[PDB]
Each structure stands twice: as C-alpha cells, then as structure tokens.
Amino acid sequence: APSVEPLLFLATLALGLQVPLATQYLWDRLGAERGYVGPNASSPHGCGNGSGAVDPLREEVEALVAHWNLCINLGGFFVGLFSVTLFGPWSDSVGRRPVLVLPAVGMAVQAAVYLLVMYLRLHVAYLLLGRIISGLLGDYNLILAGCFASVADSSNQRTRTFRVAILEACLGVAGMVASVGGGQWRKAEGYINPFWLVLAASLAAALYAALCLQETVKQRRAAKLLTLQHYKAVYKLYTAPEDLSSRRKLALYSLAFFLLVTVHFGTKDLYVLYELGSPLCWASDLIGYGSAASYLAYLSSLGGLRLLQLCLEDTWVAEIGLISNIAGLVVISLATTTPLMFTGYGIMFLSMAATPVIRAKLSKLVSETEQGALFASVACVEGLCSLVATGVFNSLYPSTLHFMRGFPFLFGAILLLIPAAIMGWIEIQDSN
Amino acid sequence: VQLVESGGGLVQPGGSLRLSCAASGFTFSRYWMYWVRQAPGKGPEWLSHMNPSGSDIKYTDSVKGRFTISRDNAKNTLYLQMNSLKPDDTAVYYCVADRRALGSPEYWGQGTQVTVS
Image (cartoon, rainbow over all chains, first blue to last red; front, side, top):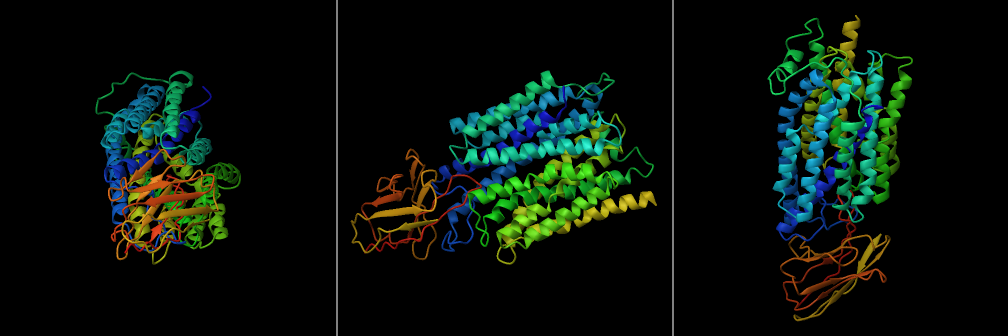
C-alpha cells in the first residue's frame, strides 16, 4: 500500500542470505561424501597460511562445489528465462500483484525445500529441485521485474530515474543487511539457523504482496496466460516497433546494462577473496567494514543521483558514476595496503548511480503498457550477467594471481569504458 | 594471532605423542579447530576438526579411532593425542583455526615436526 519497495527488500534479503548458506551446504555435503575434514573455504594466500603446497582433495572439493553451484544456477536461469518473459508481458495485461505474489511463493517453496535438504542432509541434487520449482513460478528475477515495472507504472517521465534509484537503493540496503547480518550469523551457529530467515523473509514478502500491496496497473485488461503473445511481446519490443531511431538505443542500452552489471557482480565476489589475500590479510572485522562500505555506495548514490540532477541531465550523472567506479576499481587493483583498499571503497561513493540511470533510460523508451515486457527482458539480462560475471571473474582471479593480483578489478574497470562510451555517444548523437 | 604447537619430536613406533596448540590473538572459543600434517614430499593430509564446543568431531580414515582431538577453551590449548604411531606418520603437524564460514580467514600454526622412527 505504501509501495513495492518492501517486496524487493525482503526478496533481496532472502536471496543474499540464500547464496552463501547454499554454497556452505554444498561444501559440507560434498566434503563429507569424500572424507575431507578440513576448512570449507578455498585455499588461502600468504601470511603463513600454508606451506606453499597444494591440496589435491581440497581443490577437488572446491571444484565440485563450484560445478554444483554452476549446475543449479544454470538450471534456475533457463527456467527463469522461459518463465519471466511469460509472466511479465502477462503482468502488464492483468496487473502487478499476481506477478509479485507468485514469485514470492516460489521463493518460499525453494526455501522450504532447501531447509528440508539441509535438515535431512539429503543429496545436493535436491537443491536443484527447489531451484527449478521456484524458477517455474518465476524467481527473484520476476520479483525484480515486477517491482521495477510497478515503479515505472506509478511515476512521471521525469521522476523515473529517481524513483528507480530509490528502489535500487532499497535493493542494496537489503544486500547490506544480508551481508552483515548473516555474515555474523552464519559464523555463529550458522548454516542452518540463519536459513530460517530466508523462509521467513520469503513468507513475509508473499503475505505483504498478497495483502498489503497496492496494484498500479491502471486499466487492467483480460489476458490469457500461456498464449505465446507473451514471448512475442518482448520480440516486438526490440525488433519490430519503435523504428524512429529508438530501436538502436534499446540494443545499445541493453549492451551497456549487460556490461555494467556484469562488472558489478564479478567485482563484489572478488572483493573478500582479495581483502583476505596475501599483502592485505584482513581480519574478520576489517572485511565486515569492507562489505558495509561496499554496500553503502548504494545509498550514497541515491543521494548523489538526486543531488546531481539539480544541475546536470540524467545521463551525465551516469557518466560521473562510471568514472567513480573506474577510479575505485583501478585504485583497488593497485591496493597493497588497507588505506588504499578503503580509499577505493570511499571513491566508489557514486558507483551505483549508473545502473538506475540505464534502467530508467530504457523504461522511458517503451510504451506505458510495455514496462512489464521491458523489465522482464532486463531481468533475464541481469541473470545472464550474474552467470557470466561469476564465470569470467572466477576464471581471471586464479590465473592472474602470481602475476598481478587485482588485474580482475582493472579488467572490470576497462570493461566499464564501453558503457561510458555507449551512453555518451547515445546522448550526444541524439542531441546533435 | 599465532597458534604455537609443541608436542613433537623423535618417538619410536608405538608412541603416544600429545600435540598441543596454544592460541593467542583471538577468542579460541568461537573458532573451529583442525589438525593437518604436511608429510615430506606430499601435500596437506587434514586429520581432524572440532566445533567450538566439541560436538562435531570428524576424522579421516587413516586416523579414525587412533588420533583423539581435544580442546580446552579454559586453557586455550587445542590437543591431539596419537596412538600406534607408524613411520608413515612422519610429518609437520599444523594447527589451523577457521570459522566454518566462507568469509572468514584461516590461521595456520607454525607446525611441529613428528619424526616417528
């Protein structure tokens, strides 16, 4: 009834608590099945943590865990690919409440299946069952698409950038709460007890959407689910209509969004593996401060975005955001000490003002009745970006480990030169 | 933070070395405790682990019912007693201290040198 922000807050809390606990269970079960009584992390680096020798069994269990995360994530991604683009275009024809209630129920169901597997110590393949069951009903991707479409359907043309930044800042606040309230909960009797908050958060989101949420689709029509006019409505969004030079901009902004969120997703994960690296060797509290400072960039940018719009357009704000991300990811790449590592975190205080800008510039190119289809496409792109970021950056970091640590961060900074060029070119050519 | 082990040394086969590991620099009552031996010309051979209480005690097959991990949160000295020592047990026994979390560091020890012969 206030808005759809609490829905995304609870769903993001559920997802950000689910990821580390699920991979921790994968570590526990896969190690136990092979008689490996050892630490559940990857191999350490420097500061005497080891003797330099490699562990054939720990590396094998780590590879197994990475492969099983890949398997469950790809299964979820494919079923979400085929479900989000069916439930979004439908959502813009029947309303946003059903498509924000179904995925929350699916998330609660996968949380229940995960709890059943963790408590019964069942095979890790039944995690894939919960992932597919949630993915069919639309997953956290569909919560994202429905929330962004609801914000796009309840705001002006000028207010979309700020009202999307507000919701994305709520997304990141939920991420911070997950990171530093399941970070210090997963350590203390963790891995099962913190998982009850995933089910609790998903149930709370389902109840809030079903009861306390206010529908924003003004003239709700009568549409049939399972029609094939929902898969056609994302194709006749990118290729057929909007021929008046606003069809190239959809592809270019989708490309910029892909690269930008790929860089963000990869660089968050390498952050703790780097912080507790060889010349840093951060303790448990320093990396907690690091995670917090990484997840305060969200709100500091919901502030810098709103402040900078008083003098600039809504695109140069994103250009400034991409220079803050590049200065941070180049500084962090060259950080061999804690003042230089935390300066990089501080420099990225406007890093997250470019994703909401791209989302809004996409949402202002489509009709008011296609904000479901557009953000279904965007959610699918953000899932693919998560997968690609994981693969690329977890392949770069081990390889460029004895040559230059932080090269993954510098490569992410280099990749951010393409969204900046794309967005600057798009604005300059149109305004000329 | 340092975990210092001292129970090693030359013991004839059929020995009863009691390894100790005194942790100074953290709580030691919130950390899981392991035991690893890097045998000469090999890699780590993780031997045991124990939760901050003593409820989750896990071994490998080459030490099951033969090595007996133990910790004293009061004394802050993790132990490990070794029965039926064989010249296959010659190694450098380390003493790591994880948190059984994916965003927490490992604190290896210096490593004693058991030379069963």
